[PDB]
Image (spheres, coloured by chain):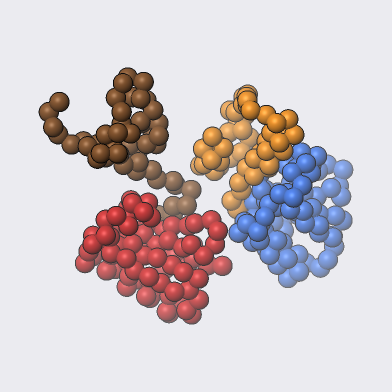
Chain colours: A brown, B red, C blue, D orange
Amino acid sequence: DHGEPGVFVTFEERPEDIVNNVASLGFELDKLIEEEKIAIEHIAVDPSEVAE
Amino acid sequence: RRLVLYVAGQTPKSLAAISNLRRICEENLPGQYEVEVIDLKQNPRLAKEHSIVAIPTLVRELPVPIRKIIGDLSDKEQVLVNLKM
Amino acid sequence: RRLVLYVAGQTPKSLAAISNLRRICEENLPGQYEVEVIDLKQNPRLAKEHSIVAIPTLVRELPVPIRKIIGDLSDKEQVLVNLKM
Amino acid sequence: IGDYDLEGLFLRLELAIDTVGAKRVVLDTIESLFSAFSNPAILRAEIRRLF
């Protein structure tokens, strides 16, 4: 509506979950990413293979 | 026997990380594995491809289960124990 | 004098477990008991039959009361004390 | 002693699933799993892997 690109940085939910959540509301996150108007970054860290 | 070291820029952390990697690899043990250093700034994409978050990182892929070590590798003994087999 | 070691695959944990079992059994003491190694992946059923949960496991059945040790047997002294009689 | 993985849990659960051709699974009283073992991080990682 206002022509501003968006970025969604998720630390818990995966992109599939993020898209499916709003799929029912009528938005098409698949299309908006397929066009890159919203970019999804799933920034997940696993402590199992992490030694500090 | 392959090791990858992800760093970003001529940062004191990354420089100390590579220097300490040199020290532990050479003085502590022989050349059992080969090291490759990647500076993330030029390729931010590779950061996403390898799923890297915190600099500096030392990742081994020789064994089937991956293992990462986060930091500048200040503790020689701990780094060697984490990389020993 | 029988000991069983349950592991799963060519895992670093299981390999280190059997190697450490070799080391503690040989260097520390003589061959008082016989070891048998079972890899659970091929027989998941045996896991249920022996009621095993966490890999790796070292179980003795010589005494009437069972005793299990969970892990890769990193601490030689603790493993020997747990298996001493 | 050392680090352990709840590998037997996965093996037994897979064996049951393949035996019964199961599609539905119920996990009852998963708090006893935490109460039994001492290391909390290992259990956390193990059941995150389980889910």
Report whether residue A12 is seen: no
* Number of marks in the rendered image: 0
Residue pictured at 64% horizontal, 44% vertical:
D7
What x and y, as percent, mark residue A22?
33, 24
Q: Is residue B57 left or right of residue D34?
A: left
Residue located farthest toward the left when viewing the structure as drawn: A2
Please report the residue visible at 40 percent of the width from the left and 65 percent of the height from the top: B4
Please state the horizontal and vertical placement of residue B16, each as a whole percent of the image: 29, 68
Question: In this orientation, which residue lies closer to the viewer: B40 or D48?
Answer: B40
Identified at 71% across, 36% down, the residue is D18
Residue D23 location (% of width, % of height) = 63, 28
Regarding residue A47, the answer to whether it shows in the image is yes
Q: Nearer the viewer, residue C35 or B47?
A: B47
| Quadrant in which the C terminus of chain B is drawn | bottom right
Q: Does B2 sit above or below residue A48?
A: below
Residue B41: x, y in percent? 23, 60
Judged left or right of residue D31, residue B35 is left
Q: Residue furthest top?
A: A25
Task: Residue D31: name its quadrant.
Answer: top right
Residue at x 34% of width, y 43% of height: A43
Q: Quadrant of residue C34?
A: bottom right
**Residue situated in front as seen by the camera: C42 or A35:** A35
User: Toward the viewer: D13 or C5?
Assistant: D13
Q: Is C72 rendered above or below residue B32? A: above
In this picture, residue A13 sits left or right of residue B61 = left
Using the rendered view, name the quadrant where residue A25 is placed: top left
Position above or below: D39 against C8: above
